[PDB]
Image (tube, grey):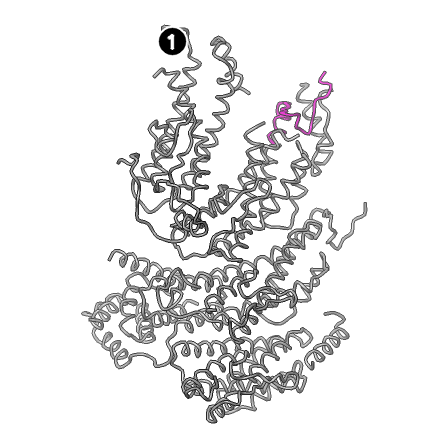
Amino acid sequence: KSPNVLLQNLCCRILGKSEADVAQQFQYAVRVIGSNFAPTVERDEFLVAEKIKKELTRQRREADAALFSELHRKLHSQGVLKNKWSILYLLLSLSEDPRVTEAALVRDILYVFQGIDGKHVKMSNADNCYTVEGKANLSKSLRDTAVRLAELGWLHNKIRKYTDQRSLDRSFGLVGQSFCAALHQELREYYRLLSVLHSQLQLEDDQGVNLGLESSLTLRRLLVWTYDPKMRLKTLAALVDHCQGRKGGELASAVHAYTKTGDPYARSLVQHILSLVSHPVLSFLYRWIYDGELEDTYHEFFVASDP
Amino acid sequence: QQSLELTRKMLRDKQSKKNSGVPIGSLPLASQEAAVVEDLLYVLVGVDGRYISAQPLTGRQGRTFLVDPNLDLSIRELVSRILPVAASYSTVTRFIEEKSSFEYGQVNHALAAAMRTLVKEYLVLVTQLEQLQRQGLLSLQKLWFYIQPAMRSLDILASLATSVDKGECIGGATLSLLHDRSFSYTGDSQAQELCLHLTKAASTPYF
Amino acid sequence: MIHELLLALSGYPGSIFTWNKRGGLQVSQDFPFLHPSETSVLNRLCRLGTDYIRFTEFIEQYTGHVGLHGIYLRAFCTGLDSVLQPYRQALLDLEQEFLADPHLSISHINYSLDQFQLLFPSVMVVVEQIKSQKIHGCQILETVYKHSCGGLPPVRSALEKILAVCHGVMYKQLSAWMLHGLLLDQHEEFFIKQGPSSKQFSLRVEILPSYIPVRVAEKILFVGESVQMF
Amino acid sequence: AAANLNAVRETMDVLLEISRILNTGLDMETLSICVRLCEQGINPEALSSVIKELRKATEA
Amino acid sequence: RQYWTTRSSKFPHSLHLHSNLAAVWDQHLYSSDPLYVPDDRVSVTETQVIRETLWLLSGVKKLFIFQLIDGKVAVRNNIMVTHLTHSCLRSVLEQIAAYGQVVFRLQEFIDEVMGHKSTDAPFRTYQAFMWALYKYFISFKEELSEIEKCIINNDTTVTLAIVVDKLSPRLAQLKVLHKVFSTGVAEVPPDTRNVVRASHLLNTLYK
């Protein structure tokens, strides 16, 4: 039944000519199709999923990448598809044109990544990091992977505390508050990536093979998931340590100093942050020019006015 | 040790110039192979396998490993031949960590990030492997078959990193290496692809 | 849970969500499925829930009933309600999307409400300053204007909106006092008070907002007196 | 049965969403044909070649 | 349709943590507290909840969940919603019941005035009072009826909060008019002449 309906649809639909009007076209199509079954290599949808992620990053649509990830969540939720690999590859081709148990371990590591201690893994302030408690329950490999992951959680906790402090004080100046708010923009992506991962953690029931899915999540999966987030948080922690006491023009120079890294990912992120921070500075300059005056309490401008 | 001193020196140079800135042998052969497969999967990310201890040799070369003495001769040989993946990954990790400081200039900086991106896809392959391992469909023969290209690529990149480190190359000297290594590996797309990628990436800031 | 969660966010605490009057909204940590991250997110959200509760209390206090009294205070409460309205619409849309897909994680809800997570504490700070200082009359108009130059784009937009409402109210007042020389006082709340009225008005500088030039003030007084005597 | 109908409906919904967000350039019937042939063990790249040559002949 | 009869309600719905919320909470209480004895509360659907609320807004005398206790609208404490929990459910119901008791007061005033003059003294001030009352209540009732009709259409599932927010301006106007009525009418005793009560309410409304 397959090939006949395939040819009929692909002729009457793709072309405005029916298969009873043009004959050799479907012949060439079926002969190209004929004598081919499937690749013998691994057909896991994870590989094509991160292929799509890479392509979307090449298209600078990481928001779209997250959206596609969530749609993949529902696609696995339904359980109505058995050959997602092939359809995903076809969609890739089309879209190119226009452009304790490891489950508990991963749940706890997610919890940590949200900035709060998990179970059997917690903030050891004696180590001033995250440490596996009751590691005899697990193996050395599990705890090593957990520590490698939870480095990101410790950085997240650091940045969250710093941003809370800077959101608290008001004598930190308008530029400092703008910096903190922009810092929260990246926290937003952090958070919704975490939400995507939590949603995919189990779906809602074991509908497929595992976690409501056909493939079980593993530490290695979380590793590739956090690769980019890890470097993002490393860059942000470096930035926050850099601007320890920089206020106003001080901070504006400090950030422009860290604008010279040369990592186009990180460099573009820093440029976005610098643009956001300078926007209040630009408004200050425009007011000082057009109005001949700008009023401040936390003197962050480069013009000092005398009483 | 060496990396910290180098980065400190070149930060000071930048400041001076720019005025700113059960026994496994008792186990059946299949079980032993599976255990070692999981261990090497761990090692790929630089975490220890259950029957292999990483030799804590750092600051002189990449991370090497020592297997347990209870291991089949053939499997021990195979793991010996396949180990250089681990050391090459430790080398690239150390390289990307060291280029963190801005004192290496953007050109060197943008260098490592490029390899960082490659690191990404490397881990992707590992994930593939672990998926196959999740399927229980992985054999050491096929593991080696898959890694052989990855083995060669990691060897190439480790050699490039070691050359840059030993020469302390910065700027066009790195590019000179890129100019040289481009010709150094004529006759194979395996190395020429990466050489072209790295030349483009490094030259973009210098261009 | 999620519906109880949003209803607590809706100002209606449940059994687990307990509203201490001054202890705020807090979590009855008794559910066997609760986890430390779960409880931490719960507390972070109860923060904004308590904020909303106190907002509602204040607005009911000084909009439904007539120190802490006058047209300025009612306008403050009305603008605070308006600014919180988009928070309510976001809450309702989140409820709708949960009612669509049940596999959604509370982390998704936290991601969504992070938009107002930062906004709410600044508004609480402003309103608690207003109340504690008992800011009354046109002084209040200056107050937010002082804070109107904040560094939080969300908070700054909300403050601009409320300040435009205040501007509209005091423009109504000024139009009344200019076009017909009519002073309207609920609790003697105006930048001009009665003078001799035999001359006719006396300025109220202590309540004059900082962003009102004195020259403008005396121009207004001159015009109003001229109209009234005519 | 009815649950199956709802599942198929939301399935087409999600596939339409991903197609539109992915600016692939297909409609409901094209996607239905593609998905119905998907489980038939059909080479994707050959399908893409066929569809691209069809679209190039369309303007020509 | 007949649902105000005292028979229990058992209905099919999606089963989740948040869909079985009340049931799950009671099970947690019982498991944590074997001392807990489940308090009998009739399970009702949000559809029935909203229909009862619409009835209260219209002022229907025959009510099941709502108890006209001492002339004030209150909740029934032997009803529950599995999607909800008892505490917040009752909180919402009491927020609604404030407006409902105001509406009850309005209804009693209306019935008093319309006695459910060419013979006694003119009372046309009261006549216009209740005339405008009726007009406003008519507008409110058409609002409620449109909501109810959308409900009866059995469309995709719609939550109560939508209607709550839609009627919130109506809730505020309800509160304002309740305060005004109590001021200008309830305060002045009927011992005074129509002159006195009329002037009192007139000045209340003018202020």
Mark yes or no: residue A172 visible: yes
Q: SS at mark 1?
A: loop
Residue where numbered disc 1 is placed: E117
Q: Callout 1, which amino acid?
A: Lys
Task: Give residue B131's position: percent from left, percent from top.
Answer: 42, 76
The answer to whether residue C107 is left or right of residue A79 is: right
- Quick one: C29 or C173, which is closer to the camera? C29
| Circle 1 crowding by C-alpha within 10 Å: few under 14, some 14–19, many from 20 | few
The answer to whether residue A269 is left or right of residue E63 is: right
The answer to whether residue C227 is left or right of residue C29 is: right
The answer to whether residue A290 is left or right of residue D20 is: right
- Considering every residue shown, the one lying at the far left of the view is A20
Q: Is residue C191 magenta?
A: yes
Task: Give residue C176's position: percent from left, percent from top.
Answer: 61, 26
On the image, which quarter does residue E116 sit in?
A: top left
- Quick one: C94 or A116, which is closer to the camera? A116
On the image, which quarter does residue A90 sit in?
A: bottom left
Magenta residues (range): C171-198
Task: Give residue E104's position: percent from left, percent from top.
Answer: 41, 25
Mark yes or no: residue A292 visible: no
- Considering every residue shown, the one lying at the far right of the view is A307
Q: Is residue D46 above or below residue C190?
A: below
